[PDB]
Amino acid sequence: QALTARFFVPEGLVEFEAQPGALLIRMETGCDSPRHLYISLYLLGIRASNVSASTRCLLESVYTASAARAALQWLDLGPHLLHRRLETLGCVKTVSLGITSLLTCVMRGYLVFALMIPKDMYLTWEETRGRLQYVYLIIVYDYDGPETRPGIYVLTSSIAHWQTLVDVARGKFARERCSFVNRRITRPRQIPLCTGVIQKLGWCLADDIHTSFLVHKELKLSVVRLDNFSVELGDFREFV
Amino acid sequence: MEANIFCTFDHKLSIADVGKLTKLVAAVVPIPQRLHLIKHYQLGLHQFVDHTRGYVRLRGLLRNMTLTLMRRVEGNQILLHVPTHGLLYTVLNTGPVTWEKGDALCVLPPLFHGPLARENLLTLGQWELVLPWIVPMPLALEINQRLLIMGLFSLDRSYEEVKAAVQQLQTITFRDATFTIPDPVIDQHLLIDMKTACLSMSMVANLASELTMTYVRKLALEDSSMLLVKCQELLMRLDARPQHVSPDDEIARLSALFVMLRQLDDLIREQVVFTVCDVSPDNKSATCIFKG
Amino acid sequence: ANIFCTFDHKLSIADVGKLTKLVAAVVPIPQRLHLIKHYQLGLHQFVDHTRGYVRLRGLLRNMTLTLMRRVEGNQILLHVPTHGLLYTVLNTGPVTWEKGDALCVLPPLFHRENLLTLGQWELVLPWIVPMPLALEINQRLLIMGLFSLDRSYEEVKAAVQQLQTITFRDATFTIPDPVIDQHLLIDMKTACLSMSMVANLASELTMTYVRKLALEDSSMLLVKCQELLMRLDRERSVGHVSPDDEIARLSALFVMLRQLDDLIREQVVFTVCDVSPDNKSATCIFKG
Amino acid sequence: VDRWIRHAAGVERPQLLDTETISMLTFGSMSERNAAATVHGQKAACELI
């Protein structure tokens, strides 16, 4: 059933990700020796504008390893673009720790297989609980400030047809779209690509969504959880 | 996953109705809730159809819903099968549109046709069964594009000027057939679509590079052909070494132009639901791959 | 499930020995059929001396993809994939692959190893490319099409010489020009002029339609959009319509953008999670 | 005066309904959340005319 995959990643990136249920992303890098480097969704939280100050302090405290800091330097080096450099792998549940760690990922399957999301990153457009829900990973670019720091969200919705979801996203994110137009006018020598990117990975039953806390090195984080989850990857689709 | 859907008829099943429904086996019907058991009211578009309100609303309501295939029936029981992405299935042509080998399919609300005498299916009391239209890509894309054109042109014009343009636009000819859009009334959904279209059109107008701006002028000066003559005839009412050439900036600008044009295309292209293998020679049935 | 193909030509020891090494490559066919003549197999039937590369791309868009693994006496066994399963593909592409890549198909641009030639017909396979390289190469080739008319000036010559090459993860290529014999092919011509036409038509049409739509409930998006248009008008200009002509203009804009859908959407067909020094070989999940 | 009335009775701020498509997808909003504790039975809905 499930399509297992296998990756290697150095110890510095692992310690908070080591909880079995996690989500993993692959990042390209211009540096020749680390051609690719593997980053979990939690590590994006240290830079995500949506994450609150306390959770950002915790993330800064945890990921102090030199390799992880170099990874964040590579991430921040990217000029106003991340989806050109980020690629989604899927959900993982197995880990062996060491000087170089081993973990497996599933790119298509539904074989506990809970997927974990940080509480800061989670939003829903609807408070009514639909019986069937899809979940998506979206990246949104802020433009009203001096330079673009990105926003990160993982959201659940009962909408499947893409254009309807883009309509509702436009409705809720009108400020970001106006900010994108403002960026285009205010700095004409610079040309941003999109306001946000939608990517699809989700099939789950809404009655199996949980709220929970997570611990690492006696540091405490608040998270939201999808329990009876199935993973189906998709293409990074750009919207305005 | 709920790989099967059962539906129960509350009304009595006369022999004629059950035979007629038996002829419909392996056709396509939509189901809103995907729940395991469903009543007979939600089977079909009759609960939601309303000629008083927008065809755009019905288009959205149809594109949002889920698709299912038909299976053989028994007393008070009708069985619906949900397709799985990537597998191979048999479907029957619900509409009169011709189907051809090797082109995609889309789902759209029903359209007016020549005789206007549409056949009625399972008219149980005041309720009726009505099927959606499965349409090959060119016709569906053309009709959605022309509906958006209707919305964009008709705005802020008197009925007199609009009257000729709507009779020119509403009629669609496709592979020897003729069709007409039922009720193209402007709706808030169409206004949102038009706002997005205007924003994308202005953005591509702005961020387009100089070479893209001046290309057709230079070539019309250089060459002369029927296509260029038509383009100039269109632009006639509107009608040297570049001082800067920069491959990297040109690459980035064209990437922005592609994201803009990609966005503008999404307003028109309905999501594919079926890709066909070769079709039976009577144009009534085909074997297709299902996509979600 | 299987698909058979039989060669009408003779095959020697060397021919089948060259063929058998493709035990995991990708081969496209016009449409699904049980038993097809070999002339239908491969992309060779479409190539001619005038119709270019973008036509090949757009036609391969709607073409179906198949896998091959067997060599009977004279029949080649094809193997159609199904969305969700896993299959092994052979790296016919000129680039190296990495775990977690998204893979796309392109017509062969610079094709010696594939040369199974018989009866002046040759087997020719499509390229397998990672997604960013595919998108960038289409962007670059399209702008090279734009420069096609100004190719006399030295600056343009240097710019197009720079644009010819691509570098990607230790590999460096030269992408051949879309121009031949100082002229441009009809297919690339129509693609480029359609893109220029849609840009131009948008430029004029935008003012009238932003004014018309803003007559309804105006919003911040509309006003900043109109300001951007005003800035464009200010920098450009240094030195009513007939309803039928109007409707023709909108139809032309949409029909020009509509044919561009062939090339702009770089649909993904494969995703890979395995790699070996055997890099010629890889295991992938089928998509698209 | 709207805010003052919302404060006077123990009622929450107003909340927009779901749109047509979402209303067709989802079967109900159940605005009145389940109470913390209940010794007596189901809260009898008392309506006034």
Image (spheres, coloured by chain):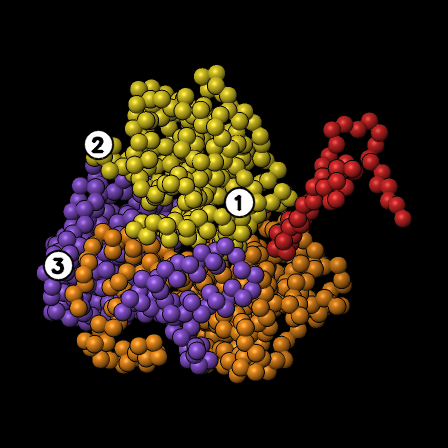
Chain colours: A yellow, B orange, C purple, D red
What is the three-letter code of the residue carrying label 2? Ser
Q: Residue at x 29, y 34 (%)?
A: A74
What is the three-letter code of the residue carrying label 1? Tyr
Q: How crowded is mark 3: few (under 14 residues within 10 Å), some or many (20 or more)?
A: some
- Tell me the element at label 1: strand
Residue under mark 1: which chain is it in? A
Residue under mark 2: which chain is it in? A
Q: Residue at x 33, y 35 (%)?
A: A76
Give the Cα distance between marks 1 and 3: 52 Å
Front-lying residue, A131 or B40? A131
| Label 1–label 2 contact, CB within 8 A | no
Q: Residues within 10 Å of mark 1 (few under 14, many from 20)?
A: some
Which badge, 1 or 2, is on the more N-terminal residue?
2
Tally of numbered discs: 3
Q: Is residue B121 left or right of residue B148?
A: right
Residue indicated by mark 3: C155
Give the Cα distance between marks 1 and 2: 38 Å
In front of the other: label 3 or label 2?
Answer: 3
Residue indicated by mark 2: A33
Q: Residue D47 placed where, x, y %?
A: 86, 44
Determine if marks 1 and 3 fall on one subunit.
no
Do we see residue A149 in this rendering?
yes
| Label 1–label 3 contact, CB within 8 A | no
Residue under mark 3: which chain is it in? C
Q: Residue A156 placed where, x, y %?
A: 54, 42
Q: Residue B193 placed where, x, y %?
A: 50, 61
Q: Which residue is drawn at 35% across and 26% down?
A: A13
Q: In this view, does C166 lie to the left or right of B252?
A: left
Considering only vertical position in the picture, is D11 above or below C11?
Answer: above
Residue indicated by mark 1: A134
In front of the other: label 1 or label 3?
Answer: 3
Q: Is residue A63 left or right of residue C97?
A: right
